[PDB]
Amino acid sequence: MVSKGEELFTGVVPILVELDGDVNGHKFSVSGEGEGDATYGKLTLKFICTTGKLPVPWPTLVTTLVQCFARYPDHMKQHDFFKSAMPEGYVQERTIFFKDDGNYKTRAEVKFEGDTLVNRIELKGIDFKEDGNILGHKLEYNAISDNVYITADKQKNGIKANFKIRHNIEDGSVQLADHYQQNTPIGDGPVLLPDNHYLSTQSALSKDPNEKRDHMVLLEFVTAAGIT
């Protein structure tokens, strides 16, 4: 046997992302479009700041801007909460603590609208330093890679996750971003509550040479692991 949510992901699925943000009162919006192919754990996305200049570095928004596209190995498919919640979807919440700086709090709803997987997000950032690495734009436009450690959250019928992102600073140092995550289903049907495991995630950041708006191109791979 297969299992209902996971059938929505056997091919290439269009993705739409919409974010409204406010970081220390600097308001902005981002839209994104692209495709995901969970068979290969593969995401291709392009994001645009629709309000003008992005007031934070693009790399700091990657994790916020669809883990339902992870490739779960066959032997791990009973541990894929994300697809099991579809098409109704899930709420994904985070707190992202930037070491020696402010924090983002995010709330997103990830669900299908027809054949399109949509991620709608609100982001609120507070306590940032005006000349710190974030509001001062001191982070290199560089890839991020790390492991998302997932555990069951029986009490919300969902999952929690934790991970670290170590963003390179232009001086050669590192800006740590400690992520704490919770996901809860939107619908009332059965979902898969996983054993402990992780998502190995690699995001490559680039620019479209023909694009004059403030933007980010991503190529991302996401693979579940940690259960032999």
Image: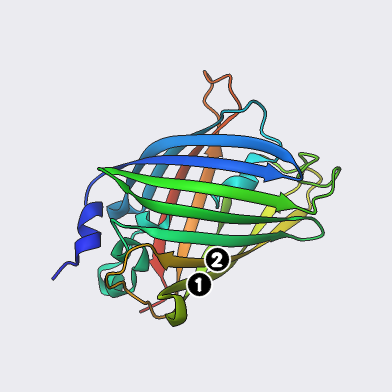
What is the distance, in whole Å, between disc 1 and disc 2 at their CAs? 5 Å
At a point 41% along the width and 53% down the height, the residue shown is 110
Q: Quadrant of the N terminus?
A: bottom left
Left or right: 185 with respect to 177?
left
Q: Amino acid at mark 1?
A: Lys
Q: Position of residue 168 (x, y in %)?
A: 71, 49
Q: Nearer the viewer, residue 78 or 140?
A: 78
Sequence-first disc among 1 and 2: 1
The residue wearing badge 2 is: 181
Q: Position of residue 119 (x, y in %)?
A: 43, 47
Q: Is residue 143 visible?
A: no
Left or right: 191 with respect to 183?
left
Left or right: 191 with respect to 32?
left
Is residue 121 depicted above or below 86 in this figure? above
Q: Please tell me the numbered disc located at residue 160.
A: 1
Give the image quarter of residue 17: top left
Left or right: 222 with respect to 50?
left
Q: Residue furthest front?
A: 188
At a point 37% along the width and 77% down the height, the residue shown is 194
At a point 83% along the width and 47% down the height, the residue shown is 132
Check contact, mark 1 vs mark 2: CB within 8 A: yes
Q: Quadrant of the C terminus?
A: bottom left
Q: Amino acid at mark 2?
A: Gln
